[PDB]
Length: 153
Length: 153
Length: 153
Length: 153
Ligand SMILES: [Cu+2]
Ligand SMILES: [Cu+2]
Ligand SMILES: [Cu+2]
Ligand SMILES: [Cu+2]
Ligand SMILES: [Zn+2]
Ligand SMILES: [Zn+2]
Ligand SMILES: [Zn+2]
Ligand SMILES: [Zn+2]
Ligand SMILES: [Zn+2]
Image 1: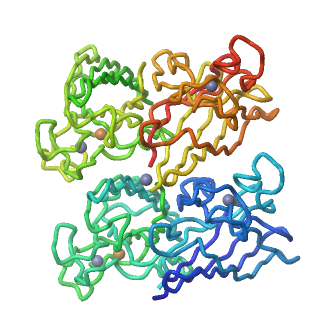
Image 2: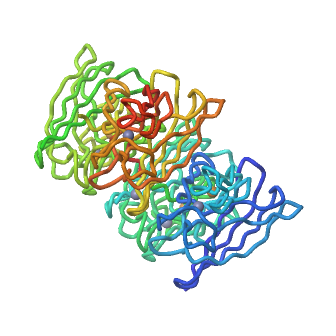
Image 3: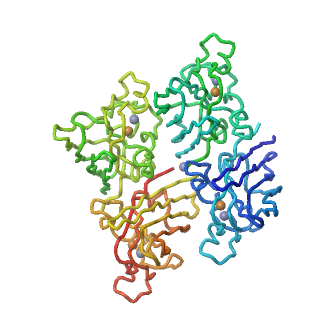
């Protein structure tokens, strides 16, 4: 059984796009992003705990962290479920990417359905930046765009 | 356990608002709404099956109908899960409403998290209007605003 | 084994006052009110589910209802845990009252600590008003003042 | 699952802000802070034992101290449950911070629900100051703002 989900990303910063999720049974989640309007280079890319946009991207809460770990890189053992690292924006301010991840299921108790994916202004230091925010947020700066992960037909 | 969800409504019409859901354990869901920029009178108010806004409110699919019944009133046995009837908009374009319902859980197999709320242009006839659409949609006309039901707590 | 809690009640309305809670062991909760700046007559008096005042009293959510019952009078089997009925305001717009209730404990899983006590603009119809809001809120109108129930020394 | 709490800060000093708490299962508590109106530099940031605001912040009692230890730094063994160290205020009088800590649960017997967060006038000396108040309050001076930790989700 395939579950499908899609986030339409908006923001006050003119960055836009979609992120498409799929998961067959209880295997990995495939996530395919198409982003525009971003500063060239690395941008923090997170699943946040909430899909509350009452105060734009600021109300989506902290990083999704059911395991109660510190902030890290996707490859790390010591990471949040929602830590999908950096996406690289081209010189035209677009990004197109597929990542596969094992901690962002689309069903069961840790489902990210109805949570928000968030693109950040700045790189995610992956917990290694030695800044006060490194080990909590990765010090990725402003939530320039976010989208609620909605069930797809 | 206390589960919360919220829909932030938007459309092409200059209509806005917030719909707050709460469910304590497996008691009924309380839905609390304040809406603006709507035409005075009754509007059909439903949970639709999908949270896909890639084609705006149109991609949110039909009334959430896990039981495979026809369209009806909230108090009827022959209703969609998503069938929450009419909300009443004042001459000032605003609606203020509280309803309880036990067919829109915020967790488990029939969870509405990551689906959508839609306010329709016209009244829901509650399946009793004897119109060709009465038994599917309640002939509630177009999708004026919708919001993905995002996890809030 | 006595637990003590107190709410300091704030409004936009200039109604204010305090509600003091005590519970010996597993016994009933005693709640003593001193209120001012209120319209003479009966006022809906509820424990709401949340102590969130980010949006003044409107963020305190619905009636505290762990049993998933409908809105009732305190003496009814079919009531919310939060349903403390009506408090009577004198001509001088003050109220002083003591009630005891066994559904608002100050510890355990259904503790009211860190929830909100709310005084409404209008009488609570105790679910017998024959209004659309009777069975959900008792149709008691605006939240004129609320206070977070804080642990007392 | 997910428990949320929120303190809306007030005081005599024009300091404002919101502190949001999230705990997933029995993991650490994330506390996310947005403050304004504060003098620049480090400020003591503590959970106090009580949510009694009848005498403003002074009635919130001492540091939350269920284990009966002395005042210390968050990473110390000998510390109060309520010891969350210093938050830095920029020259513009604002503080934005994310802290995670495993002694401030939002449920069970050591719950901080219905207690208070307090922001102090002065830096927390983390118990190291050699002052008579070092091992009790970290000599962090006045209670410049506080709020009751209200249940939010
Ligand atoms: Cu982020
Ligand atoms: Cu509809
Ligand atoms: Cu009420
Ligand atoms: Cu202190
Ligand atoms: Zn993270
Ligand atoms: Zn229907
Ligand atoms: Zn009630
Ligand atoms: Zn919850
Ligand atoms: Zn201390």
